[PDB]
Image (cartoon, grey):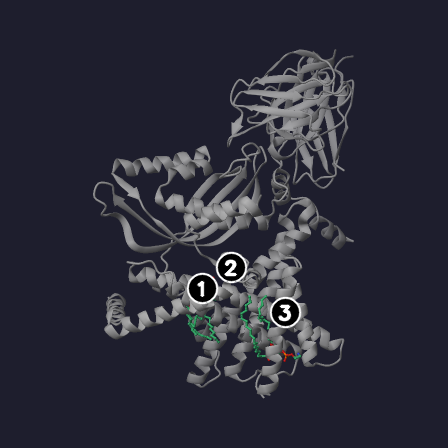
Amino acid sequence: SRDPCPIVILNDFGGAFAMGAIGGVVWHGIKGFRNSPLGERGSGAMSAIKARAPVLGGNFGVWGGLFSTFDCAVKAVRKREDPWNAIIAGFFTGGALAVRGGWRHTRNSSITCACLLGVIEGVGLMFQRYAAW
Amino acid sequence: QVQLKQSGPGLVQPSQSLSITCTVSGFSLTTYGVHWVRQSPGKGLEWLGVMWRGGSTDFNAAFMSRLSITKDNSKSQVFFKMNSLQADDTAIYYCARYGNYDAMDYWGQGTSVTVSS
Amino acid sequence: KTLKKTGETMEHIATKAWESELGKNTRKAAAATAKKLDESFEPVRQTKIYKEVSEVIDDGESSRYGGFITKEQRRLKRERDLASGKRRKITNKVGGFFAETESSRVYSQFKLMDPTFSNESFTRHLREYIVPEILEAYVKGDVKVLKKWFSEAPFNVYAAQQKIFKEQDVYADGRILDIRGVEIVSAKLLAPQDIPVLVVGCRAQEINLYRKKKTGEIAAGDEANILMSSYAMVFTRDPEQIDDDETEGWKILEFVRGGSRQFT
Amino acid sequence: GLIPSRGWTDDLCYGTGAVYLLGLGIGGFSGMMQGLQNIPPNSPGKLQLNTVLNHITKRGPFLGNNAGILALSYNIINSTIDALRGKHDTAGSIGAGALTGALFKSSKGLKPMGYSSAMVAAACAVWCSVKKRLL
Amino acid sequence: DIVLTQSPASLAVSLGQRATISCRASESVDIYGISFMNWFQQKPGQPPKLLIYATSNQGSGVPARFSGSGSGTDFSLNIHPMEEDDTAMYFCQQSKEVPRTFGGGTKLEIK
Ligand SMILES: CCCCCCCCCCCCCCCCCCCC(=O)O[C@H](COC(=O)CCCCCCCCCCCCCC)COP(=O)(O)OCCN
């Protein structure tokens, strides 16, 4: 199933980077196609991909790579497998990446991400409950 | 290419209505607008109304009570109408698509309208 | 006051360590080796291979990620380039993808004006020259620069604000510390004349403060209060005065500052 | 050994994330050294910290995102030219590197091809030697 | 709205020479410093043809011999060199404000 916890961090840093870079190729290839002039829609999609796909890979890569690091930090400390591991992990990763914006933006981004992971965890829990029936 | 084609009646009876349909092709009415311009021989080119690029209309103040310009995006048609025509309304009616800087770049062939009996 | 008091202890501890005889000597020794390390590798940098290899790894594309280009290094770089360098139903839905749009009308017009224009080419020019030149003038109250770039509508708003400051005898001396996110947000047609404009956004770090003209003490803001403001610019190009040396046609129709938040 | 390599996506994900973190750490450290030399004199503590962080968070993402795209394209190309070739060797990895560097600088010209394709192939050569030595 | 007075009402010049047609807007037709003065050409049996837009920009496919100048309230159209083909009726059209208004027209001929 899942690889060892102190080593999946590389697989989540690179698996999220691949999700953002490919996700930023379709997003910015389409966005760059719509924008550019009539005779340069294919050059404007290549230019938009090259400029913005790496950036989205890093944005995804560090969020999905820090969330995995804090997930192993919580798991190796809390020593359980409850779905509050991803709640606390999502709490610290949203406030770590928003640390330059002050101690009020860090708090708001921590609460936002923890609540955001609450909805995701809740949807999964409700999904299996319906599937049980 | 871009092409505006009009289908209206000549020889309109006095105090009757005039209806030109400007079937456009090569462009979509959602991204472009169509001015409606008239050219009398004794009064020269004059602007009647417009179907703005967004889809709202605006008319000349001297004709606003008579004009009615409506479009239909799906059929690529713009409809023009005047409620009442007198002898001074005999002219040639053009639909002119406008582009950047309101440049009436493409024009319809013109509908030579006569108002008599 | 726990955070503020701890910050003072942390700042003082670093200040004591930085000013410590052992710490200062270690920093000087480390700095001295840095000068020697650069000097030792200095002949390598002079090699033609290093210029090409550095132009492959960096190429100057790292400017997308931030940085402020100082006014002197901004004018020299510009004049250098200008001297040598710059001198069924699914098929129907697929057909609508390739159809002309308001964004395509705007971008095609600016391509008519300059055959070299593209979103990538202008975003590079915005990021390296235009946005830093305008933001730096905006925070420092440089109306000579903003007269060229701003239209009569956004400049008259600016020069009316600069008249309020002159009434209270303060002058703006701000700073730009980092500019990020320089992008063409949108390309719209200003109705009802269909004036093609580019909406440009950015996020600049900046220190906003005003000093009394007579004395020079603080009159607003703080000398260390960094703000992460967002700027919206509306750009259009004039077909005349496209041979202008500074603006080369480009003009700012709207300039809005918003979304200012603290940063560090 | 380490780095589970059961599939081709685990190669594509462990490799992209190990080189992304090498770009971040190297780029961040290279920026931090640069940001300590660009501190204006007589600046307060909040600006000196801001000055260094601005260089860390510009060279960090720049080399991290550039090393991650090269590790994506390499792993996609390496896996692709393993399937057609039917096996993996050091030569197949080197060819996946030089071809990755060429596609990296497609728009830059032909002189950038050689420099880029030589560096990426050399980096794969170092990786292929480190891979054999560690395993 | 804006009354575009166009002079001269008629003009006759020989082939290869420069023919200048003037327009004089009652008000200023500038928005954001761009003067919205379009120039049109009309052969007797055809719709008007856009020559110049935004006071200087050639229409799509318009020959380079048609030059638009002027700003503020005084504008000009220069045909140089003038060919035998471009004898027609020339109009100036302001696109600043509604209603759009056209000039009186200038009949341009051959000597
Ligand atoms: C502007 C760029 C600046 C970049 C600065 C940082 C560069 C870092 C260079 C690091 C060099 C050593 C790489 C260590 C990688 C460790 C990977 C551990 C996990 C792992 O085994 O993933 C492998 C992929 O590695 C790999 O994919 C690594 C090889 C590819 C590296 C390409 C990117 C580095 C380019 C450096 C030169 C830059 C030139 C810029 C023009 C799997 O693969 P496998 O071989 O087991 O597969 C077999 C068939 N599935």
Secondary element under disc 3, as helix, strand or loop, is helix
Task: Give amino acid for label 1.
Answer: Thr
Rendered image quadrant of residue C23 = bottom left
Residue E99 visible (yes or no):
no
Return the residue at label 1. Answer: D57
Q: Secondary structure at mark 1?
A: helix
* Chain containing mark 3: D
Residue A43, relative to residue C15: is it above or below?
above
Q: Amino acid at mark 2?
A: Ser
Residue designated by label 3: D118
Query: What amino acid is found at the position of numbered circle 3 in the picture?
Result: Ala
**Which residue is at a point 67% across and 50% down the rendered structure image?**
A41
Name of the residue lying farthest toward the left: C215
Chain for disc number 2: C
Numbered circle sitting on residue C62: 2
Q: Nearer the viewer, residue C142 or B34?
A: C142
Label 1 Cα neighbours within 10 Å, binned few <14 / some 14-19 / many ≥20 = some
Between the residue at mark 3 and the residue at mark 2, the CA separation in whole angstroms equals 22 Å
